[PDB]
Length: 276
Ligand code: NI
Image 1 (cartoon, rainbow, N blue to C red):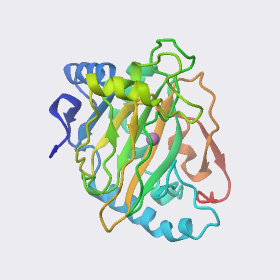
Image 2 (image 1 turned 120 degrees about the horizontal axis):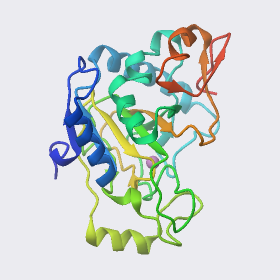
Image 3 (image 1 turned 90 degrees about the horizontal axis):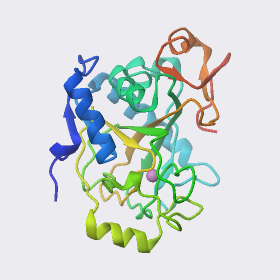
């Protein structure tokens, strides 16, 4: 069992680091190209993650009261958006300079964030099937990345509370008849891959940010703790990939809109209801 993120996937920062130096950026990119997953430690201040964790746990009762609680694949992996109230929208989270340095270098200067969502993994949750969150664009074709998932754990993720299983290097795999309509990986391909490059799972401390290819094979797993495990999730896409805009209150337009760290946003006059 791993006690920490593996050194080969990890770059250590502080919240004062606003850019990676050239050698660190090169390493970040080499990790993403080879392994499809990069763990950045020490990115976000406690003040921010505390507030986001508290807001998501406070919203959970409303989410659980809905008629059909929306889940990712199997019981206990609840889809839950974080609030888009002005007081909980932070430049260092939505427009993190290190994250965008990386996504600009991989996806281009006009890459844009188009997801502001989350995954609440409840106590007693089930095992998800191995899947990709975003598909390859044509079957049987090798092509470069068009999207990067930016995952923000809001508590310490442990082997006990449902730290995600990742399949390193799987982001480039796209043989024929590999994926079903839900993005789940066909069992024959899973087992062939396992023999060559087995999956890994490891603790990730709150304050970290995980950047990964949207095509990376992974699965959520059971949370065997007594506490819900919140993840905040964003996804950067090439400018040409069609996505609906993120609904944001126009009280953040001044700093969101016109930044060179792009967001595909629609700005609204009221407060936005993130939950319904
Ligand atoms: Ni997933």
